[PDB]
Amino acid sequence: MEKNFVISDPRLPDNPIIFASDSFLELTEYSREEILGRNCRFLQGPETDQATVQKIRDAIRDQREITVQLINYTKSGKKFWNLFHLQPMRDQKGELQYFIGVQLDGEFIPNPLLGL
Ligand SMILES: *[C@@]12=NC3=[C]C([C])=C([C])[C]=C3N([C][C]([O])[C]([O])[C]([O])[C]OP([O])([O])=O)C1=NC(=O)[N]C2=O
Image (cartoon, rainbow, N blue to C red; front, side, top):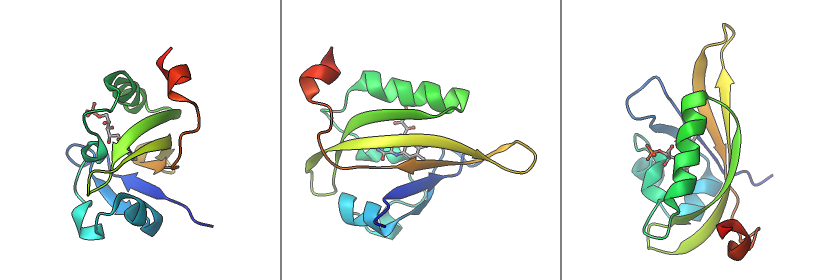
């Protein structure tokens, strides 16, 4: 199963990605050494809806599941639609340890419906 996913560690500064799957690398055109330690926002760009980024911010603050459709950018500047499901994962004692993200490439909901 081709699974594009990244993991972030929130107990380190600015929630850096600590692991990215090969499907995520092949999708974003970045090398594995070019993503680790960075916040995922670098995929964002001029066309990224800031109102959607704000929702991701609230979901991380409140540590709950969210699903959003975003526009991200590859290393070479290409423009794709990212269907992204964010989800917390906690240790045995109920403390947040990581965030996992699951990506998907394609224009699922048409943009005129997403703008309303
Ligand atoms: C990004 N994937 C992604 C994966 C995880 C596990 C997490 C926690 C976040 C993301 N983001 C969002 C980014 O890291 C950040 O949380 C948001 O931009 C909001 O933060 P700020 O402080 O800037 O408002 C992802 N963002 C993307 O654009 N693409 C992903 O694949």
